[PDB]
Length: 49
Length: 49
Image (cartoon, rainbow over all chains, first blue to last red; front, side, top):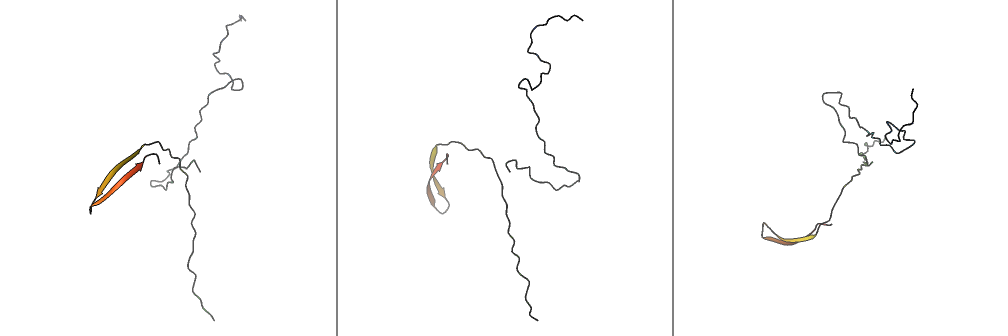
């Protein structure tokens, strides 16, 4: 209603990563199902393979 | 008729792993080792090898 000029601000509530560097965190999770009472389980994934 | 036995079994196995280790420095050190049966040895351990 009052289209007045505002002050400069670096505080972008959520600026796109297409305009600047932005932190993201999406760790991959490996599941090892245990459907039975006594399950057959493998050794942890050897990520280096 | 000419008989002949079954063969022996010959299986070939192929396994392998990959690891990530970390090692560090170490100065050389010495000592003398005494063991049962009057065993005596001069020892030199290379903590960097």
